[PDB]
RNA sequence: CGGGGAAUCAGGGUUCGAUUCCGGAGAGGGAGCCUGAGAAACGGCUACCACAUCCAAGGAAGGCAGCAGGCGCGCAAAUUACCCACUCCCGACCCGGGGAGGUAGUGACGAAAAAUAACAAUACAGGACUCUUUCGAGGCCCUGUAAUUGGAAUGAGUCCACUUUAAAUCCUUUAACGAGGAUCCAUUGGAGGGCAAGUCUGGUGCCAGCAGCCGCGGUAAUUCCAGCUCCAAUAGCGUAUAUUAAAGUUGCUGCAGUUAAAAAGCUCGUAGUUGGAUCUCUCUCGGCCGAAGCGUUUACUUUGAAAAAAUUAGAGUGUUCAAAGCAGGCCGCCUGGAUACCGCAGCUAGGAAUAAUGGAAUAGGACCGCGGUUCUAUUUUGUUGGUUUUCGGAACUGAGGCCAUGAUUAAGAGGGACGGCCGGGGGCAUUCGUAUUGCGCCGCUAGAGGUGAAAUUCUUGGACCGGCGCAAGACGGACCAGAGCGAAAGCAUUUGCCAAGAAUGUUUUCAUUAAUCAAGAACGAAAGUCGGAGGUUCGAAGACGAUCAGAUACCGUCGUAGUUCCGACCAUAAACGAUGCCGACCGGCGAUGCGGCGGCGUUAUUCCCAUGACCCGCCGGGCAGCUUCCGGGAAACCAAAGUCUUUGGGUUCCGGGGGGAGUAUGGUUGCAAAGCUGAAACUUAAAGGAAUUGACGGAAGGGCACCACCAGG
RNA sequence: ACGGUCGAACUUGACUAUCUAGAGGAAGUAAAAGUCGGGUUUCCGUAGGUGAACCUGCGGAAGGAUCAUUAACGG
């Protein structure tokens, strides 16, 4: 069941039962952490770093190899951005829909989906305010929206 | 969404008892579910079972005998003092001769007669007969 | 009737009227 | 379905009182307009003065002229039609005499053939209709 | 007025509590005061207001919601009696006083007990035991009629006395009198059904009447009015009204919402409610123990102490029994005057499952020791003035050691990435297709139109028809399917741009961020309303023509608003699955749409490789279908409308017999139309739902007959 | 007696709410037998037609009786 859609997908990952590093992976945790460091220096989200490590380097799961997950490694090194990844992408999508609605005035479908994206942004910001990742006075504004991205 | 995993487990066990199946798969598992099924086992009602450990919430395969008539959860978990347990075992149990209110107390999860013996009260979880 | 003071005023008015009639019929 | 939580006592009692207001007896008892429209003012009996005798036609399948009297109640002045029960009992009533009236049976509802009549006379000139009908007492004037 | 409590009640509950015990309040209405320990006192005072009393007319006096009593009011309620003897209270007080209170009077509020006969012999009558094949024969009880007998036994009454008591009355105790049925005489409601008890007799004749409800009465009334008889309760029994149970018809236990009353048009969303796995007691002071912290805190559960008496439950106890009461029992003694229950909140001390919550992630984190800065030690520097006694304690700090140093997992929960796709999803621009209508020119002709018939209409200034063009506005057929997409309303000509989106794939990321939602918001067919533009078709209103005892709708020609666009409003539909949303479980099947995976083969004129089009199987979410004795249901039917008296997964709206009525009125919104919210008086015994039979069809097909016809006599 | 204070109550307008008299207006009821005399399947929302009914326009429902046909598509 999707949160704002009538669909009910089952598309998701399935981790194996084996939590151990495979034998053929001849990488220490240190080299994997350094690879994460250079990918962050290129400038990417933790999801993109995980995908790049999965596809090309044979690292099936970073937290089985290093013992920590990617954004924590970034935050301990100091390369994590100030606003979280999913919230940043939600704001960017809302900004794109805002630009399209400033272009086209009669599009009601865009207005409806814009309302949905704003609601997702508010719920995620409420969660990050509870967990003290965002500042408590953080707020999403219609006008000062593209300044964050 | 899914709440009350004990309710899911007891419902699936009942619905396979009415169809007369030999084994039931209940997912997800819990400590509360395991203590409940243990209580149902020690009175010969449910039978011997397995806990499958996937690294998430596990699954349980329960071997069934044809003995269970009704397996039920009472939700919410009402606070049951010992003075008001009699009204509960009048409302839920089919006889004074058999059937069980499972309740959780600070001595553990038990049935109502053991709570009478141990002189405690608790919260109602279910009943089975 | 509404407004409790108004309905008590109405009752006092009606008492005065009927009691005036009684005092009329008792003088004769 | 019903909310069944442990902290839902306020929703349950609020919903019960709002939905209580949809009952006919509860609304007739507790809203206050049925007691203000009742000629008796919530009394089992009332005393009145006969204004008229009236013959009221029975509802369609029965055919009769039920004998009633139009009375004016002493305490509030409201007007009532009241049935006089047994046969020949209308001859005991004259115009402008005190009449004790009770309910007919159905608590504000019309009873039987007689249309619109909620009331029956019980006493005339402080002797009962039963003693007058069975010849046990006599009425003065 | 509030509590204690009362009525009812399976369990949960509903209703009452003016009222004698506890608390408050007030003395006609306010307001102010004196005195006093205490009063904003009222059987104290002072005003005003409203009442009202005596007056010699100047003045004077008032306060029953104390006891009795009266008027008034009403459906609704007692004596203008006796006493301080009891219980207690006041005073200077063993003595005085008390309408407090006690005692009688009234008293069918209500509660307890309890008469109106009992018996025997005879005469009929049953049922049993014995003997008889049976009939019968008896001694065994029982029964009423007794229009039969008979004495026994009593109180109701009348009445001395004792007793009781302050004096009495009553009760209790006692002499005398007191009972045969015309007396010492039982009522009140009923007798069709519900609901026990008559198809009896006379009267009445849809009248009079009865009848809570169904109904009875119109000439044979089981129902009215009576007579007889029977039934029910009984010193009581009817009626009216409020209220409780019946009512699982208010539903927490525990209802319902496809077709019976009922799920919001759709989606977002705050409060509210609910929320997935996960973790097994000790250092100092005092006598093995007491002190000191406890332990992140609770919620929960068990204990304890506190919670007036009366009431309620309940122990004891022959009030002559009982309702009651708190007494009593034994030959001066012996004893009683228990006990429980007493929500919630608050004190208390154990338990630690369940459920919240916290504890180290810019490490200014623990535990040890090594140090610094500042503030301080109340005693050891005999008596001191002292600069210093030392020691020891608090707050900011520098490194070091030490911790297995410190991050539960990755939900067939959710969000976000990423990948290749997919679709009448949306917006803007653009392309095309016919047809229609109009216009121009050309051809040939007198009709063309409409209808059931016509007529209105057009038309040789040349209609209709045929041809070649031009324009305008509309609309995107067939292809088009139980196919797709969207939150719903909805959505179909090409191309390009614009931004979204489900599903699928993933050994990606975050890690509970979620579900459902009062309030609040976005969108919402058609019609309609304000502004502009446009008008091809169609077309409400409207005009004509036709049509009739009485036609004012149907029908035909014409035609306005509209129908089209752009910007605003409006917020309604049979806005439908007449079916909330989210999660789980309970049978089978093969088609289809998208995505993915595995695999022989055929095809891209035998394809040179991958790739598309087909073919076979699997997986996932979709639109549907078929099959089923899963189980449900009033059923029709439904794999949900199932997992429901074996009743509890979370949550939203919402119904409560039919009408009056979605009406009035108020509020709010709208330019208006209207939308949302939404009664009551009154009226009514059924409205309604699913099935089941088939009178009569003015429904259809057949067969037969000179009592039917045909051709005739 | 001045002043203050508490403060009943009074007077005047407004906003009310009640009680109680009323010229007249517009109705019904009983008395006058007085005078004259064919169509629709069933609906929904909206607009028009003289208010509603009903009819028509526009957009929706079924809560309205599926017969027949359908294996090749190659030369």
Image (cartoon, coloured by chain):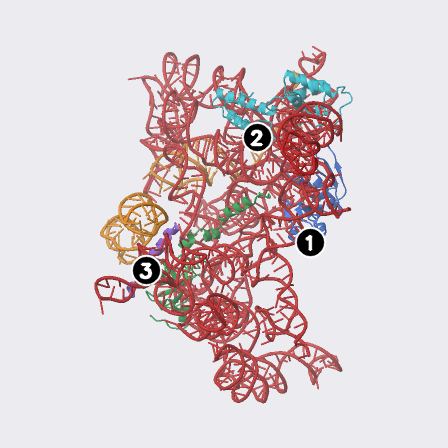
Chain colours: A cyan, B blue, C purple, D green, E red, F orange
Q: Residues within 10 Å of mark 1 (few under 14, many from 20)?
A: few
- How far apart marks 2 and 1 lie (CA) works out to 52 Å
Q: Residues within 10 Å of mark 2 (few under 14, many from 20)?
A: some
**Left or right, E505 with reference to D44:** right
- Seen at 57% across and 24% down, the residue is A90
Discs 2 and 3 lie in a common subunit: no
Discs 3 and 1 lie in a common subunit: no
Of residue E205 and residue E499, the one placed in the foreground of this image is E499
- Seen at 51% across and 21% down, the residue is A100
Q: Which residue is mark 1?
A: B95
- How far apart marks 2 and 3 lie (CA) works out to 72 Å
Q: Quadrant of the N terminus of chain B?
A: top right
**Front of the two marks 2 and 1:** 2
Of residue D94 and residue E172, the one placed in the foreground of this image is E172
**Front of the two marks 3 and 1:** 3
Q: Would you say residue B20 is visible in this rendering?
A: no
> Where residue E280 appears, x then y in whole percent?
73, 39
Of residue E138 and residue A140, the one placed in the foreground of this image is A140
**Chain on which label 2 sits:** A
> Where residue E442 appears, x then y in whole percent?
38, 12
Q: Which mark is residue C18?
A: 3
Q: Secondary structure at mark 1?
A: loop
Above or below residue E538? Residue B117 is below
- How far apart marks 3 and 1 lie (CA) works out to 71 Å
Q: Which residue is mark 2?
A: A126
Res. F40 image quadrant: top left
Res. E205 image quadrant: bottom left
């Amino acid at each position: 069941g999707r949160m704002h859609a009538p669909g009910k997908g089952l598309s998701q990952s399935a981790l194996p039962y084996r939590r151990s590093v495979p034998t053929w992976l001849k990488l220490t945790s240190d080299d994997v952490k350094e690879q994460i460091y250079k990918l962050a220096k290129k400038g990417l989200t933790p999801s993109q770093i995980g995908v790049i490590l999965r596809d090309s380097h044979g690292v099936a799961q970073v937290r089985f190899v290093t013992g920590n997950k990617i954004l924590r490694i970034l935050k301990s090194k100091g390369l994590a951005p100030d606003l979280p990844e999913d919230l940043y992408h939600l704001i960017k999508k809302a900004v794109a829909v805002r630009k399209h609605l400033e272009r086209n005035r009669k599009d009601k479908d865009a207005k409806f989906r814009l309302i949905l994206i704003e609601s997702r942004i508010h719920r995620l910001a409420r969660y990050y305010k509870t967990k003290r990742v965002l500042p408590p006075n953080w707020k999403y504004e219609s006008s000062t929206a593209s300044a964050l991205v | 969404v899914r709440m009350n995993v004990l309710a899911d487990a007891l419902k699936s066990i009942n619905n396979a008892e009415k169809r007369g199946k030999r084994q039931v798969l209940i997912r997800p598992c819990s400590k509360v579910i395991v203590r409940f099924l243990t209580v149902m086992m020690k009175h010969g009602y449910i039978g011997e079972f397995e806990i499958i450990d996937d690294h998430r919430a596990g699954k349980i395969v329960v071997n069934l005998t044809g003995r269970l008539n009704k397996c039920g959860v009472i939700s919410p978990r009402f606070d049951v003092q010992l003075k008001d347990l009699e009204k509960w075992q009048n409302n839920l149990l089919p006889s004074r001769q058999f059937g069980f209110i499972v309740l959780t107390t600070s001595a553990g999860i038990m049935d109502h007669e053991e709570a009478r013996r141990k002189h405690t009260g608790g919260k109602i979880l279910g009943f089975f007969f | 009737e509404l407004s409790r003071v108004d309905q008590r005023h109405r009752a006092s008015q009606l008492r005065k009227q009927k009691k005036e009639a009684v005092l009329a019929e008792k003088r004769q | 379905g019903k909310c069944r939580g442990l902290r839902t006592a306020r929703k349950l009692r609020s919903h019960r009182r709002d939905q209580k207001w949809h009952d006919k007896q509860y609304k007739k008892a507790h809203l206050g307009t049925a007691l203000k429209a009742n000629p008796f003012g919530g009394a089992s009996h009332a005393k009145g003065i006969v204004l008229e005798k009236v013959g009221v036609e029975a509802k369609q399948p029965n055919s009769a002229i039920r004998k009633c009297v139009r009375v004016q109640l002493i305490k509030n002045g409201k007007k009532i039609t009241a049935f006089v029960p047994n046969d020949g009992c209308l001859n005991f009533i004259e115009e402008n005499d005190e009449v004790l009236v009770a309910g007919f049976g159905r608590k504000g509802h019309a009873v039987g053939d007689i249309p619109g009549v909620r009331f029956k006379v019980v006493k005339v000139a402080n002797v009962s209709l039963l003693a007058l009908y069975k010849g046990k007492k006599e009425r003065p004037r």
